[PDB]
Image 1 (cartoon, helix red, strand yellow):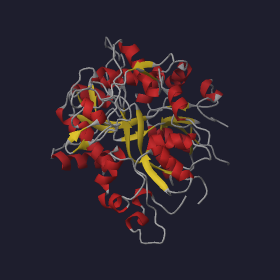
Image 2 (image 1 turned 30 degrees about the vertical axis):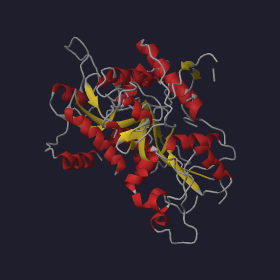
Image 3 (image 1 turned 90 degrees about the vertical axis):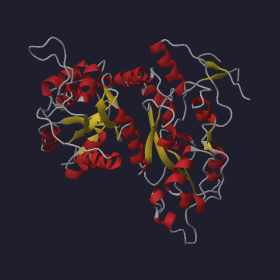
Image 4 (image 1 turned 45 degrees about the vertical axis):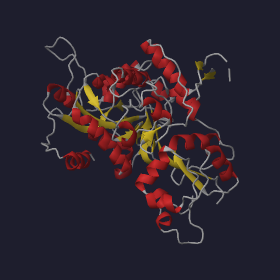
Length: 211
Length: 246
């Protein structure tokens, strides 16, 4: 999806591109790492702030923590938040108000990808510091490992974005998604602060919504 | 008409009280920012398009600097954002179809329906009461001028009259903005059905506050806006102004 968007852009405004991945395999967050004074952005956003890449093209959740220094255009797509779970006939969570969601326990293993926007949102989410502790003690290092664990019942629940989790559950089956879009958000683009091209990209985003 | 907890909005048509979900959002933003403001009321039209190359209504005020801030059903598009900078869309919307209740999902595949492109049958789907000089009208005109031209004979004036005609079965369906159609369907009695897909929405967009082109306060406000999203402070308002019964 991101590859298609970026090639469409490169065909649109005629910009050459050098595509590369990130070694850490994490989005990044403000973490006061060892031998450091304050919290420093990590992952892809950290590299973009450091100027390693001109801009980030990834399924990134729009959050004002990055927007303080990263320019964000209109979201490329819209999504929400749900929980992948192996609820099949051969109640874990009936919704956002489920007591199991409210009350942590060792019966379920709630997990999210380490250094993720959802993790930081849960950290800043009030009245759910217990959920943050559950994340800290049970976070999955990646979305793929969490999906595999839920598919074969190692992980009882995996909180994840609505669109991607729903697509994965549909594609691999043997799994279900619970909880409605309790946090509506969008996946857009992230560029350096005051990037002149980002505005154009925003327009291009609308073009995609038109196209 | 001139009730507490409502902003006193002056109607300078060429002193009422205004209250609503967007009004509450604006009030919360003002409290978080501590900024004064009047409440300009758009009277000559609702939003206004480039009428003969000249914008009217909402854009006619803000773009021509008759107004500075802008709130409401401000659809985000290239034809609107090129001249007026748009904030982050606080709410999402798009294009959906308001149809009758469960009495006669049809074979329509949305705007990509073969019957739309080939309306040669006895009773093809047409006659959607699109509002004149509306955002969705411009969207369908740009995307499919031929489709709109073929069905141009319909009931333009009012959304509510279109709802009445749909209740009376005069019009088979009406394609309009996703958010308003969804709210009306959730609120209208008789369980008026959503389009062929409950979650199906075409050309998904959002609604954002249209500040002045290059406004310095644009960047902080969005942050403050998402600050609500930081604490999910708009959930109850969204439930109040979106949830329905039948």
